[PDB]
Image: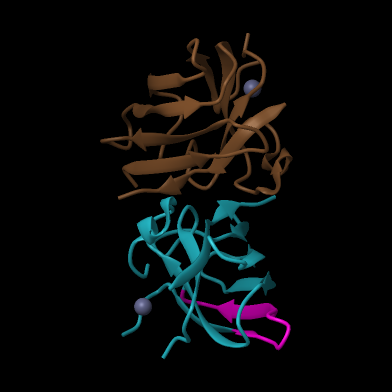
Chain colours: A cyan, B brown
Amino acid sequence: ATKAVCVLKGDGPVQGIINFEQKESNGPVKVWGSIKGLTEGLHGFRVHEFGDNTAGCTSAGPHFERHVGDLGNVTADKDGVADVSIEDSVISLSGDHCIIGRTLVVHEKADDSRLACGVIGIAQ
Amino acid sequence: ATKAVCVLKGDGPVQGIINFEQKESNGPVKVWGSIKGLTEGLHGFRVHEFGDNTAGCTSAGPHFERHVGDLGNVTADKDGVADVSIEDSVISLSGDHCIIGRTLVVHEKADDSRLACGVIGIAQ
Ligand SMILES: [Zn+2]
Ligand SMILES: [Zn+2]
């Protein structure tokens, strides 16, 4: 399990696709993609505990203060677009800190209300 | 991972929520829920390899004759509703036969077009 993908959707205009790649167990996770429809500026970007979208982003639960799921912020430009490119060694695509089957969420405000989310699935 | 859930959606009216529960990692998986918007009769019900819905159900790829993700059929009644209740000892919510982060699909034809799908996520 070295690749994953998430389709972000919400009740507003936020939309995006986020890819994850992890070539080696324990090794870093590359996280990259693009999100549009945001207000200009910083937005919280987190993996939440449950891949449960039966009630939208609300059923995703709490963060998977500092949590393993706190990826930090994405940045939207004046056009409302955030190009994402992160390396993170705290999340994983295997083992205990595995984020597969969990939910990725983009928040209304900056890290240090849930605008869009999707369940993180295994990719080819 | 002892519980999972999947929200099924497509381009047409097929929609529903499927729950999974596995008390013990060796034991069977209970699968239950409801899907509406189906033509009366049998429809193929399968877990496909990738939890990738960037291109709708198409990107979910192949079945995860007999494959591990081949759950059988669901039956829609005369109102187009399939009430699902099954116990499956082939799939799992952990291990090599894990379906978390893969895609559940309901099909136009019976197992003997992908009408809706969703990525299977960890549930509380
Ligand atoms: Zn946190
Ligand atoms: Zn098959």
> From the viewer's perspective, is A13 left or right of A47?
right
Say above or below: B95 vs A72: above
Kindly tell me whether residue A81 is visible in this rendering: yes
Please name the residue shown 52% across and 18% down the image. B80
Q: Which of A5 and B10 is in front in this view?
A: B10
| Direction from residue B87 to residue B116 in the image, left or right | right
Is B15 above or below relative to B121? Answer: above
Q: Using the rendered view, name the quadrant where residue B90 is placed.
A: top left
| Residue B14, quarter of the rendered image | top right
**Residue depicted at x 58% and y 17%:** B43
Query: Which residue corresponds to the image point at 60% horizontal and 65% vertical from the top-left?
Result: A24
Of B1 and A60, the residue lying toward us:
A60
Residue placed farthest to the left in the image?
B23
Q: Relative to A50, is B48 above or below?
A: above
Where in the image, quadrant-wise, is ligand 1 located?
bottom left
Residue A85: give x, y in percent of width and height: 67, 79
Percent of width and height locating residue A90: 46, 76
Measured as percent of width and height from the top left, residue B111 is found at 62, 14
Position of residue A35 measured from the top left corner of the image (x, y, whole percent): 66, 72
Magenta residues span A75-90
Can residue A85 be found in the magenta stretch?
Answer: yes
